[PDB]
Image (cartoon, rainbow over all chains, first blue to last red; front, side, top):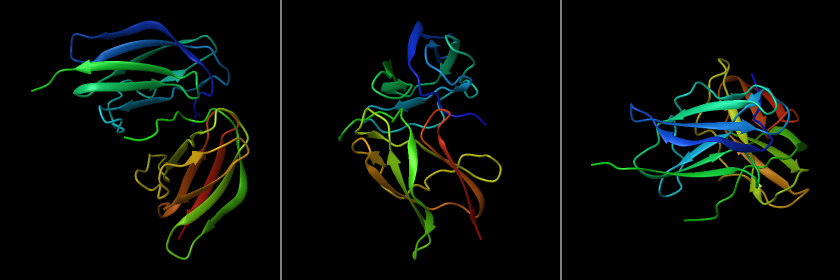
Length: 99
Length: 100
């Protein structure tokens, strides 16, 4: 339906835990080609891809300078979340404790 | 343990049209016209139902090594109509493949 956003993102609101064991982050799309899909990759402690942990139904950047809400269920341990493409990609770290 | 690259933001073009191989796969060759290389080639494969299709990328994770570099991409697309998208943005290459 849509293609992935080629542009830059910035943090509108810092990543935060929710009441039900998920995380939310708000991001601002500074680039062009909107409406486009927000690129999101989640990797685990070994930098292996982790699938199906994106709770929000596929995140879009609707316009230029639009703000997008992103809900995730990151996995156990240290996870690495990358948003966007290219050099300017946002790189976020999260830690979740388990058994 | 390995290199950590990001996805290529730039434009791609077809260096060589998608073609069937002798061993039940396809190959396509693509040229990276953009910047930030070496970066990862964005590749998505969807089926007739527009549903993601997993583990059909045979090539070990495809990279664009340099600017104007040519990357060989081997895939095992599913039966029927598949939709392959390469790169990001408006200029993303959109390929429709039909397999019998």
